Image (tube, rainbow, N blue to C red):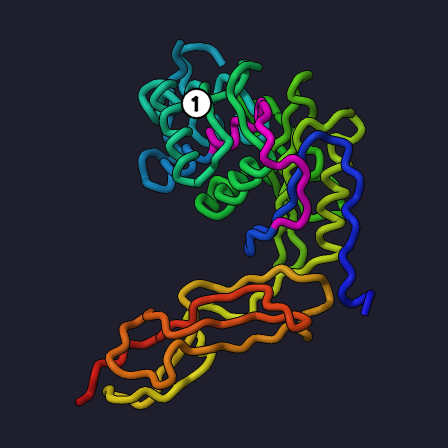
Amino acid sequence: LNIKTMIPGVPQIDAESYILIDYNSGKVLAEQNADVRRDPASLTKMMTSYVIGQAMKAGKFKETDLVTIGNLKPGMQVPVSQLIRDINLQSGNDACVAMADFAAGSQDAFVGLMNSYVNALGLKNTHFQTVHGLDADGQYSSARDMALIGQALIRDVPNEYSIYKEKEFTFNGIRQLNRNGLLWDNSLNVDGIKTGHTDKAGYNLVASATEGQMRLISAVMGGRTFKGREAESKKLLTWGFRFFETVNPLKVGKEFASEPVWFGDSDRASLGVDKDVYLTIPRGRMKDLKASYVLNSSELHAPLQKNQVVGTINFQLDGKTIEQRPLVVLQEIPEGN
C-alpha cells in the first residue's frame, strides 16, 4: 500500500561517515559508519565552545569581561565576546588557549572539563587532548558523537549556539567572516555549526537547519573532495526534510486522558506525560498517527503522587506502535478516606 508505507532510499554521500538526526526526537534518519573513530580536527572547537558556554551560563564570566593574552600578541586585553567569536566563526587557535586559561586556570584543566562533559553527554567514542585539536594526532570522535555535541550546544547553551549564525564579526577593526559557507545558501535555513579540514581528517561539517518547527542535525566526516564540502551535507538535510516530519503530539502538563480514582480526595485523575512527546515520521502521515493508552491496574486507587506512572501511551502508525511513553498522574490525589 506501497506509496504510503514506502521507505525512501538514502542519497549517495561522498564521505567516509555521516549521520542525520532530528534535534527534538533524537531519531536517526540516515547513518553510515557513524560510530567509527576519526579525527575531528577543528570540530574539537565545538566541545571547547560548549565548555565556555556552560561557564557563561553559570555566571563565571561575561562577554564584556577582558582577557589578558599570555604565553594576538601577549599582554593585550581582549573582550570575551571577541575571543569566542574568533573561536566560533573562525576557529582561531590563539583564542582557544587564551580562553582555556581564563576559564580553567590552565589548558590541561580545560581539557579535563572537555572530557568530563564527554562522559556527561554519554559519548562513547570521543576523547580530547587539547583545546584546539591542531595535533593531527591522537584525539578522536565519530559522526554520531559530533552530532550529539551539536545537539547539546543547541539545547544546553542557546546563548553560545546563537553566535554560530553570525556571518561576520570584527577582530580589532579587522573584519572576519564565519567560515561556514552554508550560512549564505538561500535554499536552506542553516544556522550552524562547524566546518574543518585536515588532509588526513578530510572535509568535516556539523550543520543544523530548520524548516517549520523541525530541526535537523547532520554530521559528515572524512568528506573526500573540495566541491562536496557543502553540497554533500546540503543533500542530506534536504533529503531529511523532504521525506520526514517531526510532530509533537503531547506536551507536558496537558491532560491526555482522565480516569476515575477510588478512595481519594477527588474522583478523577488527570493523566499525561512528564516529558514532551516528539516523534519523527514519514512526511505527510500525521493524520494517520493514532495514540491510545493502557493502564496497569483496572481501578486507580488513591493515593497517587504527582508524576506517578499508571500506564503507557502507545503511538501507532499502520498498526505499528512506533513509540511508547509512561502515562503519569499530573496532579496529586491524597487518599480521602
Q: Where is residue 286 in the image (x, y as percent from the top left)?
A: 67, 70
* Residue at point 54%, 14% (across, down): 137
Q: Mark 1 points at which residue?
A: 78
Seen in the picture, residue 118 relative to 107 is either above or below; the reply is below
Q: Can residue 115 be seen in this view?
A: yes
Magenta residues, start to end: 28-49
Seen in the picture, residue 207 relative to 222 is either above or below; the reply is below
Q: Quadrant of the C terminus?
A: bottom left
* Residue at point 54%, 29% (across, down): 141
Residue 32 part of the magenta-drawn span: yes
| Outermost residue, left side | 337
- Front residue (pair 188, 288): 288
Q: Quadrant of the N terminus?
A: bottom right
Question: Which amino acid type is marked by label 1?
Answer: Val
User: Which quarter of the picture shows residue 192?
Assistant: top right
* Residue at point 62%, 25% (across, down): 175
Q: Position of residue 12 (x, y in %)?
A: 80, 39
Q: Position of residue 291 (x, y in %)?
A: 56, 75
